[PDB]
């Protein structure tokens, strides 16, 4: 379960970057570890 | 002239960077002091014609995302005027002269002269490569052609040379008015891999050393001086940090204008007038 799915646009001398952040609640009995990675195949984001 | 150090650096760095990266043994020589694995990984990734990654160059503040794997960001800096001439007269000319040029050319026979043809009208000839003419050779320049006596030189009827010369704009008198400026540009090699940042630093220093011999910064942009910053995270709050090591390139150059003089005097005349008091 995922909440607060913010894009977090930044505009910099190097160019644009996304630093967005979200809050996730796991399933029971899981030990998520630092820099573990998630993808959400149902959800598509627009980019240019 | 008026000059733009940033656009000069962009125009000069991009082709040189490409021509080094397409040539494996050059990188193998530049990176000889690095750790073996750093060297081989860089050469595998970015170097040679088959390289799947690529480096990029551009000015700061673009509106789009860049290739943060390896990107040279060019960033126009400070400057100040340093030395002035009396009357601000940087020079004077009898014939409005353009940029300096070097062009390859070949001799041809024409009417028992040898001639070299050049793409533009020759305002001044500085050097015909590997030739010093005697008075007997009857060296003459006319329009966009250099001409050279055939009689004793028949062996050279197809000789290949480089001509160093400069354009003419027009036949006019004037004063070059201006001053010298000392100006800074910063360049930083961005990468999210620190070993790539260190290799991009090495490659950039090599490129600038090679650049010191170019006609552009021999005639203008003189006294290249380099300073180097710490390696640091440029951006720190992505999914990963982006690192870079700044370098500052400082140049001394002339800012000036062609003040043309329309006044010309072609005859004095004398008269005596009598004072009867």
Image (cartoon, coloured by chain):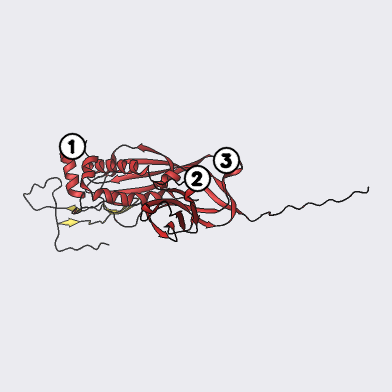
Q: CA distance from mark 3 to mark 2?
A: 11 Å
Tag 3–tag 2 contact (CB < 8 Å): no
Crowd tier of the residue under label 2, counting other residues whose Cα lies within 10 Å: few below 14, some 14–19, many 20 or above = many
Same chain, labels 2 and 1: yes
Q: Are marks 3 and 1 in contact (CB under 8 Å)?
A: no
Number of residues whose C-alpha sits closer than 10 Å to that of mark 1, classed few (under 14), some (14–19) or many (20 or more): few
Q: Which chain is yellow?
A: A
Give the Cα distance between marks 3 and 1: 51 Å
- Residue B75 shows in this picture: yes
The x and y percentages for residue A21 are 23, 52
Quick one: label 3 or label 2, which is nearer the N terminus?
3
Asked whether residue A14 is in view, the answer is no
User: Which residue is situated farthest in the right direction here?
Assistant: B277
Which mark is first along the chain, 1 or 2? 1
* Number of numbered discs on residues: 3
Which residue is at a point 11% across and 52% down the rendered structure image? A26
Q: Are marks 3 and 1 on the same chain?
A: yes
Circle 2 sits in a helix, a strand or a loop, which is it?
A: strand
- Chain ID for red: B
Question: Which chain does tag 2 point to?
Answer: B
Q: Nearer the viewer's eye, disc 2 or disc 1? A: 2
- Give the number of the disc on residue B254: 2
Q: Is residue B79 above or below residue A9?
A: above
Q: Can you identify the residue that label 3 sits on?
A: B85
Helix, strand or loop status at disc 3: loop
- Where does the image place residue B138, in percent across and percent down from the top left? 49, 51
The disc at residue B237 is none
Along the line of sight, the residue nearer the viewer: B125 or A3? B125
Q: Which residue is farthest front?
A: B151
Name the side, left or right, on which B68 lies relative to B142. Answer: left
Q: Which residue is mark 1?
A: B35
Quarter location, residue B158: bottom left
């Amino acid at each position: 379960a995922i909440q607060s799915q913010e894009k977090g646009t930044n505009q910099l001398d190097i160019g644009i970057l996304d630093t967005g952040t979200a809050i996730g609640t796991t399933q029971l009995e899981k030990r998520i570890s630092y820099r573990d990675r998630f993808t959400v195949p149902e959800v598509l984001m627009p980019q240019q | 002239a008026i000059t733009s150090v940033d656009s000069y650096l962009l125009s000069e760095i991009k082709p040189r960077l490409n021509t080094v990266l397409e040539n494996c043994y050059i990188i193998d020589e530049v990176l000889k002091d690095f750790d073996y694995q750093t060297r081989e990984s860089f050469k595998e990734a970015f170097c040679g014609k088959n390289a799947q990654h690529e480096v990029t160059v551009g000015f700061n503040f673009p509106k789009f995302k860049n290739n943060y794997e390896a990107h040279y960001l060019i960033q126009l800096g400070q400057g100040q005027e340093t030395k002035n001439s009396l009357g601000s007269i940087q020079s004077s000319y009898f014939e409005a002269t353009g940029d300096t040029l070097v062009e390859s050319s070949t001799a041809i026979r024409e009417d028992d002269k040898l001639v070299f043809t050049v793409s533009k009208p020759i305002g001044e000839l500085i050097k015909v490569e590997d030739i010093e003419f005697a008075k007997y050779d009857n060296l003459q320049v006319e329009g966009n052609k250099v001409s050279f006596k055939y009689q004793t030189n028949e062996d050279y009827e197809n000789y290949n040379a480089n001509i160093i010369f400069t354009e003419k704009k027009n036949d006019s008198k004037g004063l070059v008015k201006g001053f010298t400026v000392e100006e800074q540009v910063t360049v930083v090699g961005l990468s999210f891999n620190v070993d790539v940042a260190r290799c991009l630093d090495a490659v950039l220093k090599m490129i600038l050393i090679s650049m010191r011999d170019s006609i552009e910064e021999q005639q203008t942009f003189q006294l290249q001086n380099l300073s180097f910053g710490d390696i640091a995270p440029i951006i720190e709050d992505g999914d990963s940090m982006i690192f870079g090591r700044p370098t500052i390139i400082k140049y001394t150059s002339s800012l000036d204008l062609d003040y043309t003089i329309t006044q010309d005097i072609n005859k004095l005349t004398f008269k005596e007038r009598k004072d009867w008091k």
